[PDB]
Length: 310
Length: 273
Ligand SMILES: CNS(=O)(=O)Nc1nccc(Cc2c(C)c3ccc(Oc4ncccn4)cc3oc2=O)c1F
Ligand SMILES: Nc1ncnc2c1ncn2[C@@H]1O[C@H](COP(=O)(O)OP(=O)(O)NP(=O)(O)O)[C@@H](O)[C@H]1O
Ligand SMILES: Nc1ncnc2c1ncn2[C@@H]1O[C@H](COP(=O)(O)OP(=O)(O)NP(=O)(O)O)[C@@H](O)[C@H]1O
Ligand SMILES: [Mg+2]
Ligand SMILES: [Mg+2]
Image (tube, rainbow over all chains, first blue to last red; front, side, top):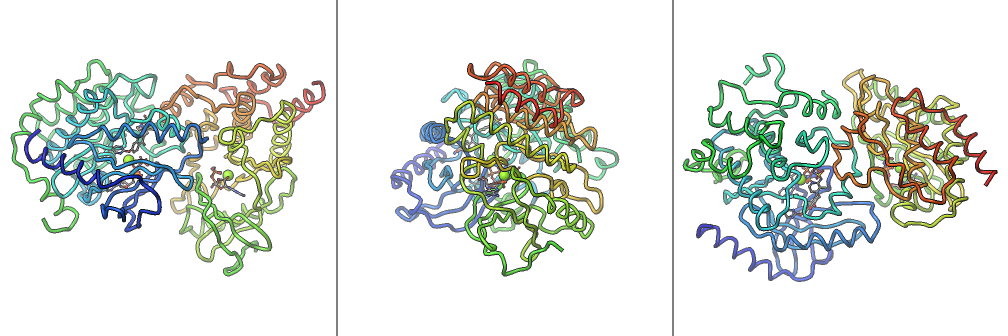
């Protein structure tokens, strides 16, 4: 915890104190940010305090007993205070929708940045891997919770060079309420979880590796690249799940990326969760020791990719 | 030409979105339901197949079937059906927690199979049967909606509507989950979905209540490893009803009975009670 991070952490608690009870009338809608199948997110201004925050709106059709429990369980996010976890202002329910208010990350998710970038450099993914590993560690030690949903759309970045996790399973009732959702298109779900209860933070590490491969090549790696598609450098949802379980895991191309990076993602994609590397081993991996020593300008690379000045 | 022009449909409050559209409460010689479809720019090959399916959905008038009033293409492609008061069956069982008698529960299962039997008699596969698409009109008659419409579900290439998998996974049959048949949707796939609806009525819960992973359900149900826990059927439910539920939930589709047999079963235990 360096000085520039302790400065920013303490600065967030100060603006957070300026926010009291969160009412729906206290917000003015500025612009829409994104819309997955979880909910829709807006950039809003909190009029009683002028703070600009991101407001996620989840519309669940659950009974009020389960819903009031979700709001109660989400208040643990007031305790999550790390430079690798997205800030949390307060959650509430109104007009048939749960509103989770979190800090605004003007860079967006890495899933959006990947679209504007095509591919992401290995030197940048080195810093992203450090933040995800540090983010999963803080959730594992200081709160004993998993993330359960590591994917590019849950890794958030901003213009100040920060990389943070969000949308992690903190509310057990919210996790079970989301289980009655429509089918998605792609899955980042570790093969053990697809088949029965997870192997703790190991199962989050698989998703990080699968997210790294997708951002490194600019394409969802299931199934792996076809013919000459790799030298150029519509599967069903059930077949993707059957592939992850009963097929060899994906891998980086052998010629484009360093061996330290190729071995890093290969230790993260071992189909056996026990043979898979844990946070202790990945923290001292060769690719991480190197990428941590490199002085890469992440904030400048981000604003260049989006089209803004640095 | 069952098409409705512009300025005729007063679009009002936004209600919500589902597997293939967003519903608004509209006005059109009375309250209607306007579902703005997710296929905004249809292909002229997709458009003619949609008009063809509306023609079949048009000639369907049954008491347990929501009235299909046609479509519109002026602002965007949409669907106009009858607006029904009260809550859906999903709201009653899982949100409001309405406490029906066992007689009323069996009666809901009878009218649902009755309407489904009419749809199959006219050779229409629902493809999306669930308690969300079952409304209790004035807390008496059952009304099934969101039936058919296989062409506005699963986006087109240019001329190859490959049946694509969308909807709620809790009601999808295993052969539907796999999509490895390219015509997995069948009469028995609707029968299976009807079996899950029976599980809702007889247990008061949704299936797989102890599984909170979406993709785990998709994989294990498609692999035959996972099945609804029939132990959760409440004590006061008829034995003849619990056996009928298990016949609709058979993993292989050819073992599932058809609705002429299902409706006959329900009315038999409806009398002897
Ligand atoms: C795909 N994984 S799963 O386990 O099957 N399903 C789920 N996985 C993870 C999680 C959930 C549920 C869930 C969501 C979606 C969530 C979203 C925003 C949020 O607010 C927030 N604010 C600041 C920082 C970080 N979050 C808190 C949240 O807590 C939750 O429990 C699954 F439902
Ligand atoms: N705090 C934020 N700041 C900037 N952009 C955000 C923020 N939160 C979410 N977004 C964007 O909003 C979009 C939708 O978010 P979301 O509602 O969680 O769906 P998703 O996570 O992308 N996919 P899914 O989880 O399946 O619904 C994402 O692509 C994000 O890039
Ligand atoms: N004909 C209707 N009359 C009144 N309310 C309706 C009607 N159809 C749908 N609704 C409501 O509109 C909302 C969304 O419905 P809908 O778009 O059909 O999603 P869904 O039924 O839950 N899933 P799906 O039908 O497979 O797309 C729900 O609250 C429904 O109860
Ligand atoms: Mg997300
Ligand atoms: Mg419906």
